[PDB]
Amino acid sequence: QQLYWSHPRKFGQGSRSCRVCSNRHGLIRKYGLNMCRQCFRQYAKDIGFIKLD
Amino acid sequence: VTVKDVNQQEFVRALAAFLKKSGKLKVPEWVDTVKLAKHKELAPYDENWFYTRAASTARHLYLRGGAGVGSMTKIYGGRQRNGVMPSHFSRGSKSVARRVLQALEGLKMVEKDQDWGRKLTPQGQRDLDRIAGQVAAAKKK
Amino acid sequence: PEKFQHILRVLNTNIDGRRKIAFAITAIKGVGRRYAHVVLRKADIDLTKRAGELTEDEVERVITIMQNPRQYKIPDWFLNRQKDVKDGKYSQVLANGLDNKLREDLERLKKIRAHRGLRHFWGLRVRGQHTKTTGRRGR
Amino acid sequence: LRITTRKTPCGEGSKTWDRFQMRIHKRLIDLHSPSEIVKQITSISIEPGVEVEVTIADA
Amino acid sequence: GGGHVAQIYAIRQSISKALVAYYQKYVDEASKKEIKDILIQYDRTLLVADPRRCESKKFGGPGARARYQKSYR
Amino acid sequence: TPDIKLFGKWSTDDVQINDISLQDYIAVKEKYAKYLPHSAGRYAAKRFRKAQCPIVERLTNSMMMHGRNNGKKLMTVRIVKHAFEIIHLLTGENPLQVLVNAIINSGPREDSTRIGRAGTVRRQAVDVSPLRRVNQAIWLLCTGAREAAFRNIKTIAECLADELINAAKGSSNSYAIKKKDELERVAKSNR
Amino acid sequence: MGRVRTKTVKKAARVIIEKYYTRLGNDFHTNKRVCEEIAIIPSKKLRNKIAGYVTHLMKRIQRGPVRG
RNA sequence: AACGAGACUCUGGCAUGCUAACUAGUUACGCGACCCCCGAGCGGUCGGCGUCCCCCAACUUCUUAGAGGGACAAGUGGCGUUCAGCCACCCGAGAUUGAGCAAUAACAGGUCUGUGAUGCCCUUAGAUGUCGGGGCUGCACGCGCGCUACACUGACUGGCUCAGCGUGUGCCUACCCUACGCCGGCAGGCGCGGGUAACCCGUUGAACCCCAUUCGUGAUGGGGAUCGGGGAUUGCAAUUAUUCCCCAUGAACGAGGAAUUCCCAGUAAGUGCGGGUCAUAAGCUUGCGUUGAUUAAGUCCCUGCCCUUUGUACACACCGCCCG
């Protein structure tokens, strides 16, 4: 078949992935996020936060 | 007297002179080519800057609990003009302060004590308060 | 007092006796203010007086301490040039030789015709810079 | 815990943000008594979702 | 706490009240009532305290009130 | 003296206000004399509250302007201590009486304003408050010393003490007594 | 400034004076504590208001008859 | 009668009252040790300076965070129909400290490149689904947001002295914050140790400011653009210079047209710091401290908005409509 399929991803914006579906572009790490800012908003009601200010 | 009582601008300018009389302080060769910190743009005007800075070294050890080569630099560091970029703080030289403190320790006015830092010898503490009253003897406090 | 002399000529640039010694010397190319406050102290003379108050005996020593800096124990890192390239030594370059040296390195980078010499010959910025909104002479 | 992030997906319109916050609380009661009756009585009689951590010694 | 300046007002405000308290506790009323009239005459926050502290910034400005420039073309 | 502060050396007694009009917005000695000009930072939250604070402090406030000098009130007080010192050596007076004359001589007597008629500029002459006069006179002379020392070898202290002399004795070599008379010359015309 | 009283205050203020006319004084603090016991006002700031208006009404009721 | 307004939530400002603390302090001695007679005295002691010693000491003012209280136009004087309220003053924290939440109806506003949300259409093996290389940085030009400057109220070199909001390895897949010792001018290297964190970094020993030298009205030592050579760090790789450091080179610019933005009290302005993105890297954004003014207590002139009355050939609503 092939002798390659991959090349070093060890750092950068391609070796971390966000939990929408493996979406990116929307660089995220904060306090152990790995969680997408669009959906973070939809989880304002869900637990982690309730808005108070 | 305690060194607290007197002015400190006066303190150093008599303590620097004191040392240079007594043959004290074996100085590094590099002393006429030395910028003295990363945030300067020039060498000092002073030709006896080493004597002056050793004064200020020994004084701070009298007050605070004593700390190493890192902390001395942080006390001395200032503002760095990066030109077109906005100014920021940064630390100065290290290898100068590492020669200062070892030169003092050769005279046994300081010594590596416990709890991660040099502390000033009782012989050192004697000599500070000895000249502290000499300041008040001079002008009149 | 001290009416003896004023403006003078030294190597390749005319230096006034109006200004302080260190700052006067800087006008000569290849010598900045930082380079001069060293060389004066190796020469063991005052920098606290004017350049018109130096004698001929003194300034004769200045240029020697300048042009052989390694032999008067000014460090290698403190020079303009360390291993020029294709000349094999540490060097210190002064006024009219500086320009001659400079023009060589331009010529060299069009000889090989690297990216550098092309950018030079086209009159565009050598280093990583945008030219889209930078320049104008034109508009 | 502060989180200061965009209120608008796919940024357009007037620039707005949103402050969220979580407030944790800690407090601890020090006892000195046999470890048996402590570990017996502690883990029971807790209605809400509130955490407890027992330590062997600290002093 | 504070800067070089605000410390000066703090040490003044404390020593003024310190003196008063010593008379309030070990000496009679009419001693310290007198001293109170003198200080509060040229009140300059010797026996009182400012309630003013910094306001919290909101977005769209570098300051709490000042705003970024607005362009229509 | 033991019950009323000087200035650190300068008497606030033997100081007068030589108008009946402009007193009760110029005061410096009723009990308002203090060792230094500074405040805790109360100066204004009412319209009347502005008036009360000293003239010497007001002068220090309006001295620091134009970007680089804002928020440097301690540097500003250095310039004022030299000012009085230079004024006393130079002419020999209670150097506050100099300043009081300098303020009173620089305040306008009549002023103009705008009025909209026919979409074209017309002007109308009107009068001026005592509180306006004081505010204007403090502004004008401080602009002089700021202007002069912008390329002169002379320091701002020297420039400012010169500017209070030529105001205190009118002579039209100051930026103030010039600019005062310009306004009044307009106010005569359109009236 | 501003701070013109709303209708929620003026509705209950009238009621509380009608059915507990006797308990009232003309001091702020006494009329507060009465309103705290004869009813519950679910806020603290709201309580401090309703007392003050109850006080201000009771001044006028000791003159001619109120029409509210 | 209902929704919005208000009420409400958070935050700031008032507690020598209450609650309780070696992962927080203070005071008190017990102290013994160091220090100088520096003051009475002699060096001891008494007093002064911090640190170790501190307890089975005492306390909770300071620090921390919980339960409570306090402010209501409450009192007084004017004014108002004497109603609803408004103005001044006493007490004092004055009835506005700043934010969060926010109606009906609408827009052919933005987003199919947040979405394993989704219709329809297209494409689907010579693929619009994978590796290697290049580009999004390419310039005779036009515009916007900002940063740094044009000096003496300054720059430069020494000396003194103050802070706060936070954050940190054991996480993503290979990675943190750093004290201390040693080596180097510097970037940096190297050896050891702590930190799950009011425990270690950090009593965050920051800048402006403050104090003393030097420069002298000079495109000057102001300004640091452009540009040559050399040294380090990150990475698999640094060329079209990743970033950082050293020496040299030394431009425009000497207060800015027509126009125009933003701001009312710890506010504007000056000044530094933390977080975000981050293998390496903020001139950006988001928060925080520090220094801290001048001017107003108004008005409908301009720009715009709310309510009533009036006129209309308008309703795709004056950016409208319409005439020769």
Image (tube, grey):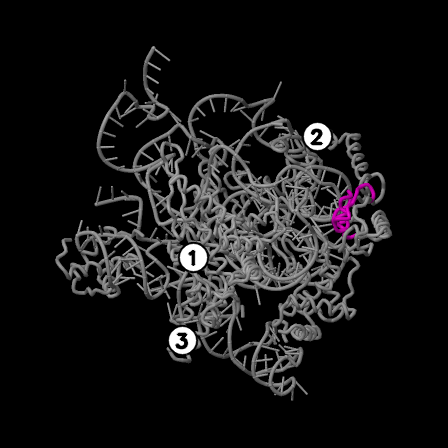
Is H130 or H317 nearer to us in this picture?
H317
Residue highlighted by disc 2: C123
Which residue occupies 41% across, 71% down? E38
The N terminus of chain C lies in quadrant: bottom right
Distance, label 3 to label 2, CA atoms, is: 84 Å
Please state which of the two labelled residues, at mark 3 or mark 2, is closer to the viewer: 3
Subunit under mark 1: F
Residue highlighted by disc 3: E32
Q: Residues within 10 Å of mark 1 (few under 14, many from 20)?
A: some
Q: Is residue G64 left or right of residue F160?
A: left
Which residue occupies 48% across, 40% down? E69
Please state which of the two labelled residues, at mark 1 or mark 3, is closer to the viewer: 1
Answer whether residue C23 is magenta in the image.
Answer: yes
Name the secondary structure under disc 2.
Answer: loop
Name the secondary structure under disc 3.
Answer: helix
Q: Amino acid at mark 3?
A: Lys
**Looking at the picture, how far across and down is residue E37, in whole percent?**
39, 71
Q: Amino acid at mark 1?
A: Tyr
Q: Which residues are magenta?
A: C10-38
Same chain under badges 1 and 3? The reply is no
Which residue occupies 47% across, 56% down? F101
